[PDB]
Image (cartoon, rainbow, N blue to C red):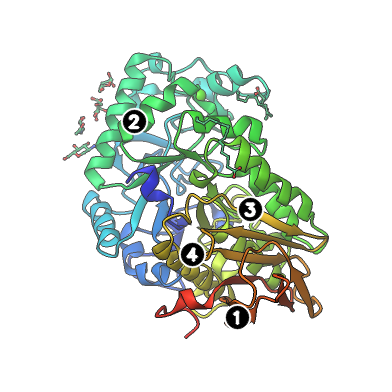
Amino acid sequence: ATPADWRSQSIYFLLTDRFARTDGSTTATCNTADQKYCGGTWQGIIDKLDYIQGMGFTAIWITPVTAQLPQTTAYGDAYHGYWQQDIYSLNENYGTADDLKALSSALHERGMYLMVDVVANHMGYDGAGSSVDYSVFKPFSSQDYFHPFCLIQNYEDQTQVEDCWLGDNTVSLPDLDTTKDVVKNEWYDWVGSLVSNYSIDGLRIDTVKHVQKDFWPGYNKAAGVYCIGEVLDGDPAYTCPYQNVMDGVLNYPIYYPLLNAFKSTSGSMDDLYNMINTVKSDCPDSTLLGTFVENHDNPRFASYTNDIALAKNVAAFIILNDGIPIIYAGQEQHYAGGNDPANREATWLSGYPTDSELYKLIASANAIRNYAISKDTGFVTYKNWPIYKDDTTIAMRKGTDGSQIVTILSNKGASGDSYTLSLSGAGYTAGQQLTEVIGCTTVTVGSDGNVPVPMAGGLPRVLYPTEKLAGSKICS
Ligand SMILES: CCCCCCCCCCCCCCCC(=O)O
Ligand SMILES: CCCCCCCCCCCCCCCC(=O)O
Ligand SMILES: *[C@@H]1O[C@H](CO)[C@@H](O)[C@H](O)[C@H]1NC(C)=O
Ligand SMILES: OC[C@H]1O[C@H](O)[C@@H](O)[C@@H](O)[C@@H]1O
Ligand SMILES: [Ca+2]
C-alpha cells in the first residue's frame, strides 16, 4: 500500500514472541528477565485479531521475521527478531511461511494492513566481533560484505554511526557495507521479494540512521510500499531530514515532549505545543510520521506513573495527532515495564480484557478518527493545529471546517478538579451542538463562539459536531 493509503491507518505494534501463543494460553509463563522465547506465533496473532480490531486499529506492525542467531547469548535469545543471520529462512519459533501468509490473508480479509519490521544495517552474532564466523550469514556469507569491525563510540560522528558496528563484544552486530553494489542489489531484491511473498502492505525499517542516506531511496523504491523508518533521535533537525529519503519516520521528535507533558502533573505543555508546530513546518510531511509514546526500546508510559487519567490523555493524543497512530501491545492494558527486557511483557497474561479502561478509551478515540476520515477526505492531510495551552492543558484542532475534531487534553491527573474551560479558536459555529465522544455528552458552542468544556477527573475530551454523527455507532 502507498504512503497515501497509509495516512488513514492506525497501527497496533506487537512483538510476535510476546503477543499470542498458538495454544491461546493466557497463563503460559513469560518472565521478561529470562530474555527467552516465550512462544508467541503468527497463528496466535490470527486468533486474536478480533481483540485488536475491537480497538479500532486498521493495521499491525510485527517484529522481524527472518531467521536469527540460535544461541542463548548472555543477553538472552533472539526472541525480538533484531539479530538475524539467514534472511532467506523464517524464524521458525513463529511458525512457517504458510502461517505468515495466512496472517497476511486474515488481516486482508478484515480490511486491515500488515506492516513488517525489517533490518538492513546488521546481522547478529553470539560473541565478540573478532570471533565472527561469517559463513553462518545467508546470503552474506563472507567478511567482504561487512564493514571492518569497530564499535560506535561517538554518536555525533555520523560516519562512525554508519560505518561502525552496533552492539558490543557480548552480542555483536556485524555491520553490512551498504555502500557496496552487491550488498545494495541483494537487499533491494530481497525486500521486493519479501513484500511479494507475504503480501506485505508496509514496512517499518530498523536502525535507519546507521545506514548512509543514499541507501534508502533505492530500498524504499524496491519495497514498493510505504516505509516508516526508525531514526532514534529526538532532534527534528536530525530526524526529519530522513523523510527526504524515506516515506516516513517514527516521530521521536514528538515522543520526548509528549511523554514529559503527561508523565506527571507538572509536565510541560509548552514543549509539546511548540514541537507540534516545529514538526508541522520543518518535517517534509508530518502526516506521514508515526506518533507513539510507548515501545520496546523505552520505559512504558505507566513505568513513569500509574495514573490512569494521564494514560488516557497520552493515548488520545497518539490517536488524534497528525500521522499514523502507533500503540504498543500492553499499553492498552496499562503495562508498566521499564527498559528492555522489562517492556517486553507478554500480552496474553493480561487475559486480553476488552473492558479495561485504556482498551475502551483507545476504542473510542480510534472510532471517531476512523469515522471522521470516512466523512472527510481532508482529515488526514489537514495539519494538526494547537489552538490552546495553559499550565495543565493543551487543545488542538484537526479536520476540514465543519467536520473538525477538537481535542482538549489535560495533565491534571485522576484527582483533577472540576471546572469549565472556555475554549476559543475551535472554529465551530455559534450555538452548534458538539458531542464529546469519549464520555458521550453534548455541549453547545456559546454565542461568543467559545466552547464551555466541562473538565473533570483529568479526563481527555474529544469534540465533534453532533449532526455529523447521524447514523454512526458513536455514542448511541
Ligand atoms: C541534514 C540532516 C541533519 C544532520 C545534523 C542535525 C543535527 C541535529 C542534532 C543531532 C542529533 C544527535 C547527534 C547527531 C549529529 C550529526 O548530525 O552528526
Ligand atoms: C522532501 C520534500 C519536502 C522538503 C521540505 C522540508 C521542510 C518543509 C516541510 C513541508 C511544509 C509543510 C508545512 C505547511 C503546513 C502548515 O504549517 O499548516
Ligand atoms: C520468496 O518465496 C520463494 C518461494 O516461492 C522463496 O524461495 C524465497 O526465498 C522467498 N523470498 C523471501 C525474501 O522471502
Ligand atoms: O539471492 C541471495 C542468495 O544468496 C545465497 O545463495 C543464499 O543465501 C540464498 O538463500 C540467497 O537467496
Ligand atoms: Ca551501518
Amino acid type for the residue under numbered disc 2: Lys
Give how far across and how far down residue 28 sits, in percent: 45, 69
| Dot 3 or dot 1, earlier in sequence | 3
**Element class at badge 4:** helix
- Which sits earlier in the primary sequence, circle 3 or circle 2? 2
Answer yes or no: disc 4 within 8 Å of ligand 2. no
Q: Which of pointers 4 and 3 lies earlier in the amino acid sequence? A: 4
Q: Nearer the viewer, residue 71 or 280?
A: 280
The residue sitting at 81% across, 78% down in the picture is 417
Does dot 2 land on a helix, a strand or a loop?
helix
Question: In the image, which disc is placed on residue 221?
Answer: 2
Mark 1 or 2, nearer chain start: 2
Vertical placement of 212 versus 421: above or below?
Answer: above
Q: Amino acid at mark 4?
A: Arg
Up-down relation of residue 30 to residue 156 (above or below): below
Q: Residue at x 43, y 31 (%)?
A: 123
Counting residues from the start of the chain, the first of labels 4 and 1 encountered is 4
Tell me the amino acid under the disc marked 1. Answer: Gly
- The image position of residue 154, as x and y in percent, is 68, 23
Q: Quadrant of residue 209?
A: top right
Kindly indicate whether the residue at mark 3 contacts the one at mark 4 (C-beta within 8 angstroms). Answer: no
Q: Residues within 10 Å of mark 2 (few under 14, many from 20)?
A: some
Q: Disc 1 designates what residue?
A: 439
Considering only vertical position in the picture, is 269 above or below 236? Answer: below
- Callout 3: helix, strand or loop? strand
Tell me: is circle 3 under 8 Å from ligand 2. Answer: yes
Camera-near label (4 vs 3) is 3
Q: Which residue is mark 3?
A: 385
Q: Are marks 3 and 2 in contact (CB under 8 Å)?
A: no
Between tags 4 and 2, which lies in front? 4
Give the number of the disc on residue 294. none
416 in relation to 224, above or below? below
